[PDB]
Length: 232
Image (cartoon, rainbow, N blue to C red; front, side, top):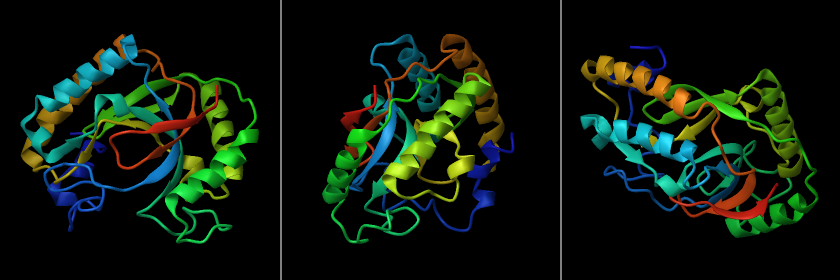
């Protein structure tokens, strides 16, 4: 069992997942939690998407899938820069220029306007480097890609008018699920063996993760991200 997978063990926690009751119910159904964000969706029908969907099925095959809240296939995305969200009306997760009680839709309008002058930045390619029950860890396909996506994020920080504490150490990922209840330790070696096998299968099938260009989106909940401004 890797250090990374052991995070989700019952032994590592004294309270349920913090998202429980806000982002999703105990039965793994997603709850209203509106916000906005910049993300790259997968390309529907692409070999990348099919590969990821196969990985996602290996996860669903596990009995502990019952303790995970899987998002829809059509929602799959890599976040490039988090926007605001109803559940986190606080600095430094909010622009200081806006009242903390501003309706989410008004923040979306402020940003749609501000993002009308977003500069053309170079394209980047990403690759999958790890797997865990919640999804895929990613980095730049090459070291130069890391530098390019960091430039996108630094530029977004200027437009959005805040930076999170992890801004410079941000872990790129694609979420396949949320943990609803922590895993008993006895099933972990099996998950590790499957994650190892599926990671290598995924890396071969999708050696770069094909995606759409970054887009500023709004959402009601984790099920769907409506593209408002595409940075293509």
